[PDB]
Length: 41
Length: 41
Image (cartoon, rainbow over all chains, first blue to last red):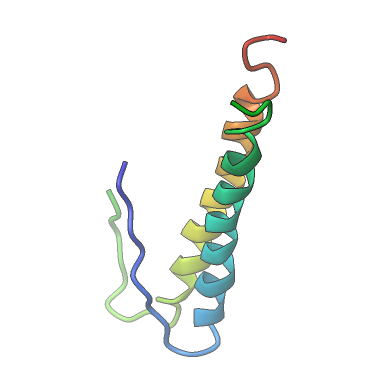
């Protein structure tokens, strides 16, 4: 499930992807961050 | 899959939030969906 959203901005509407996308990635590291080591190894 | 497109639209950047944001919400329901009863206990 490889996916890559290249940077595409025009003006003020570009800020949408920047924040939106940025949130997605952060969501992964977060959940997958503790959900991967919730009880250590 | 995407069809019916106008010859000139002043919102090509809007599609960013639509997809980006839409993905975020879906990410929650997904993870929180199985992570709510994963392996039962």
